[PDB]
Amino acid sequence: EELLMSLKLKALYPLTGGYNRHSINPFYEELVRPTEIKGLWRWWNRVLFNTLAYSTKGKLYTYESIDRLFEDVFGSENKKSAVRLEVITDEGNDN
RNA sequence: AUUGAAAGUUCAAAGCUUAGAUACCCUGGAGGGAAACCAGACUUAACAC
């Protein structure tokens, strides 16, 4: 709905895998997968949330419950994610 | 011991005849096959030393 932020990142020796477990295939090349960025963002978010909850309450919550709590930003089966990721790899034309 | 006595409102007779539940009439309007999801995890064994 509106661009929130924009991050020019840089990965060194990425080993991104596609359907053939490689960054390239007979049909396209894909060095960065937005689905992997989203999944790793959620994984790190759960790690960080248990970190917090343990540095204050000494309690640790299941991943189910953490993502159920964050389902307003990351979405779930009951709600569409509020954040939309858009990778733009420069030179990312047909290869 | 009467303006009385006596006297079957009875007989024959088809609620029948003609007549179209028909005429006009859009199952249509509104409605995203979407939402969520890491192609990833990790080296081990053997003998020599």
Image (cartoon, coloured by chain):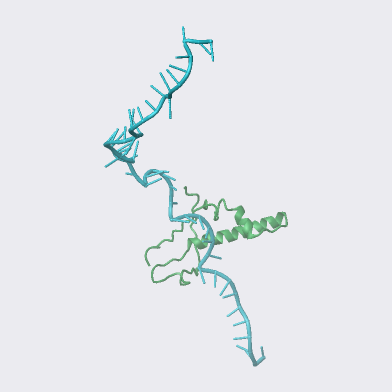
In percent of width and height, residue B48 lies at 65, 92
Q: Which chain is green?
A: A
Image quadrant assignment for residue B49: bottom right
Q: Is residue B44 above or below residue A26?
A: below
Q: Is residue B24 above or below residue A48?
A: above
Residue depicted at x 71% and y 54%:
A56
Nearer to me, A53 or B26: B26
In percent of width and height, residue B39 lies at 50, 68
Nearer to me, A57 or A5: A57
Image quadrant assignment for residue B42: bottom right
In percent of width and height, residue A2 lies at 47, 47
In percent of width and height, residue A50 lies at 66, 58
Residue depicted at x 42% and y 61%:
A90
Residue B44 placement, left or right of A12? right
Q: Is residue B33 above or below residue A28?
A: above
Nearer to me, A18 or A8: A18
> What is the count of numbered marks?
0
Residue depicted at x 60% and y 56%:
A67
Nearer to me, B32 or A66: B32
The quadrant of the picture occupied by the C terminus of chain A is bottom left
Residue A77 placement, left or right of A26? right
Residue A87 placement, left or right of B17? right
Q: Which chain is cyan?
A: B
**Seen from this angle, which residue lies furthest right?**
A58
Q: Is residue A85 above or below residue B15?
A: below
